[PDB]
Image (cartoon, rainbow over all chains, first blue to last red):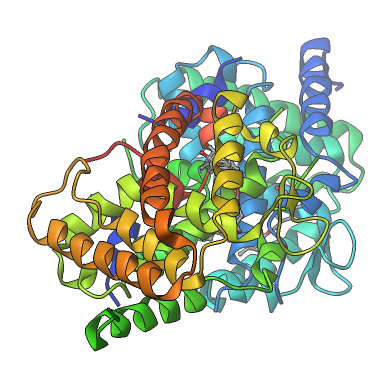
Length: 11
Length: 11
Length: 239
Length: 239
Ligand SMILES: CCCc1cc(C(O)(CC)CC)ccc1-c1cc(OCc2ccc(CO)c(CO)c2)ccc1C
Ligand SMILES: CCCc1cc(C(O)(CC)CC)ccc1-c1cc(OCc2ccc(CO)c(CO)c2)ccc1C
């Protein structure tokens, strides 16, 4: 479910 | 279902 | 008339975001898989593109409003626009002289030939170069160039988008500042805005062409294994 | 006694496979993402490991019998043994002097420090180096070393394996040639075989340790995005 995109979009 | 492994294992 | 504080605050906000996500020294390129002039450039360009996606995301997170959109919408916009933001931002390094992307030094100068060896055909490269040129000619301002990227990323007419209302607004708010700024700050830009939109239109065709070709390559594991997790995820077709 | 034709035919078959999948010049390393001495080595080592998986596969496809096994079994064996074949094959470049893996030149010489910056801890590195040393000391022959790799890859006691019968046989056929060859061709190898098996035993613990740590890293997308499609697939947990 878009692992990387989510991580990069938060922070 | 292991796309790459299959391709590399054939040929 | 003259821009307002809000309109300006946005311009400074976007410009700062771009400077923060676009390194003029290109010093990070040395860390990519080395270029090799049978898809010998695929590794290096895959790393270039992956790296660029990261930057486009960082840029988006700083666009006023975007961060308040739903995580789902953020993704929908990225996955569908990213490829276009990359084509737009790459122009900053495109050189009309040698008709190429001159980045770091000689190693990071990509000719129309180099780019051929990455899995893409003239069917895409021809219009792409055409695009870069026509755009390079608009000699846009850093503020106009940065806006254009924000307008393209905040296009509500993208598949997967839910809140097709709030986004439409944000884009509208961006499109004005551009029309205003040009009217006020760009002498001879009487026809610029309209010309810039025609560019957002060309980006859809390029987006289209690249997608077809990307699928083709993406299906052959001997080629997909050369890509990166981020490139596969963003350019993938998962919902 | 003395080896037979069959036993020998296998030895030449394995040895040829190894020479064909292990480049002594290491010239391919220059094409990996450059090493950087916060997981600065992860990119370069990920590419090293990915590259190695490719070789281990090519080697397996040439082991007599393996290719006749079911595609499913081939995968089961690879996914569970690959990491061990890599530890075994890397020994060919491990140097007791500087306690490191000296490959191409100075750039491709990995110290215990370098390897630390790839996401792994001493909890694994300590026993690994320990393993490399103890093994380097057995001064095995190219024929013994090549066999050992084939015995490890044809271990039927691996999860996912179906035909736990046919494989058990192949391994047996390999284990003999080793016991024979040593008996006949390796003076002072009266205790070698037994010592070599103890090594196949240590490989299981290392395999174990690496798997735990791999999961840890693998779960953090900021780290998994640095890996390769092949590494993710082979070291992944898909069934
Ligand atoms: C729009 C096309 C983008 C593209 C996609 C791919 C893949 O589709 C191949 C499988 C994904 C890695 C490979 C290569 C390229 C590709 C990349 C190019 O790089 C321009 C280059 C890229 C990005 C930037 C900043 O983000 C800069 C500096 O301004 C230069 C120039 C031309 C092409 C065709
Ligand atoms: C057995 C450990 C293997 C490993 C896994 C990983 C990852 O798990 C990190 C996420 C996957 C990329 C990163 C680095 C390594 C790792 C790699 C090492 O490289 C030895 C090196 C590798 C492989 C070969 C031939 O295939 C040679 C030449 O003989 C040298 C030495 C020590 C470690 C810890």
